[PDB]
Image 1 (cartoon, helix red, strand yellow):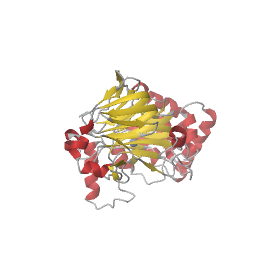
Image 2 (image 1 turned 135 degrees about the vertical axis):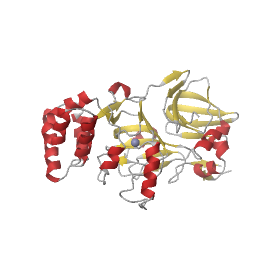
Image 3 (image 1 turned 90 degrees about the horizontal axis):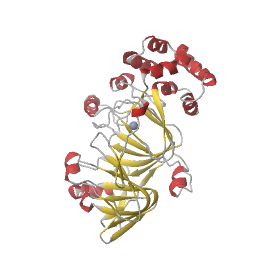
Image 4 (image 1 turned 60 degrees about the vertical axis):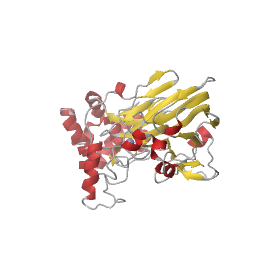
Length: 392
Ligand SMILES: [Zn+2]
């Protein structure tokens, strides 16, 4: 068939919501597993499937047998595989603070760690592959996140109340610049024993006298990470509440965390994660610091500003690994075409896809794969369809 309704995998990671995918889309969960991510792609750990003829086949296998026709020549020649994973993320508790190195450093780090025979599944294995990990989140319900350093004057204001927590806070307040921000970031994550306990005590008392954000976000995080030095991170990093339909790009070398709510996430293919708190795992502070850009991002530059052309709302992404757009649906068909493979996902309403004689209906939460050779398709109905594709 031209258009292929996807059979997608749900990752039941312990941190997933037991209800979000059911409340949103009617996805079954009678056994009440945590449902953390709904995956749409060709990931080797659990590829989406397509129906051939009766049988189902792995999308990954289907693509591997026919890369040019399925991916298009540009993506096949640049990446050699579907270059993204698209997911619904349903964060029922706050997740870890993460940084993804840039492509060059990822290549350098992947090598370093190979040339010292570090086991893959080991604690200190920072670079699992040589790829960068650009990511976009697009809010499906109100979506609370941290992303990027605050303006230095903002950090200064927020740290005043906890100046006695740690000498590195005083040091930064004395001269609030990128060097001392770096030292502060690293000192906080390296806090131990009485040093850490004193700092956490001062912060917890501040939660009694300081109201509103980001103190409220610290309170929310403390439910799940009561003894984590990452509880100070909302004072250094922007706290953003995305409304449904808003999006943000997670740049390289930039700390971020997904704290609450449901989002679509599009990500390049990498498992390179340098954690930066809100985690029980060992953190390599020097390697983290060497891969963080200590440059404020002001609040008004955090969201991706999309561009509306006809029925298409494009969210410009500054990497080649993926592109992302939203499409309004109406009675009159709209043509949705691309040079690459596409995944189309029904956000809300109901989508009728048509390619010549074939008609495929998607309800909210369902998705289809469109191979490059099958572009374009016509879409009608009501609501909105999200598309992940490549603009090369
Ligand atoms: Zn990330």
